[PDB]
Length: 258
Ligand SMILES: O=C(O)/C=C/c1ccc(O)cc1
Image (cartoon, rainbow, N blue to C red; front, side):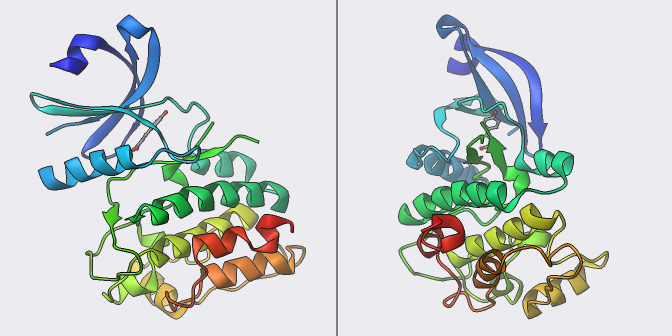
């Protein structure tokens, strides 16, 4: 079967549960890739495969091939070698508003395409944004869903605690706007280097999120601009319908500079 026929397997790049990512080479092509090897809910596997295919965009990991073998499934992507956005925040502590703004721009373009194609990711966070002034590529479509335009339903309780929308935590129906909440949380980290909602106790984390209990504490927020904090407030609006859309967030002056 076609992957163990055509490809050699090298060094592990990442690992969740379910999945391992390793560098592979298409031997006859002399071409390196990332292979997401999945260690075989078959419905959810083919969905992530279909969604990865759907999405061709500078800011979205580009699926080269999907291969089904005895016991393993391979989703092969173009190799992006710049590391998680997560790692770069750790190393640099935080981004200049200059660098934060080009970054969240990169992210909003990916989120805008996803939404235009009726895909909601639901697990936006730095670990799932990969670097190539290096452009940011959205990854891990393992939790992604398909919506019809502005439809909102209960699609299930899924994602990363720190990043989860109020609507999802209340078990209210939801859609595209949960990605914009995650973008708010991301943007806030970019600017100062910790999240808006932290707590040892998950239950109290979830109370904060549902209640929008974020501040811009002194001293570190005092020199951050009005335009930046404006975007975070519009992204971190509890009302999903009132929340800034991806398209509206690209036309925001902090992102436009126009
Ligand atoms: O969709 C994913 O989960 C990961 C994709 C991926 C693409 C290129 C890499 O270098 C590493 C991971």
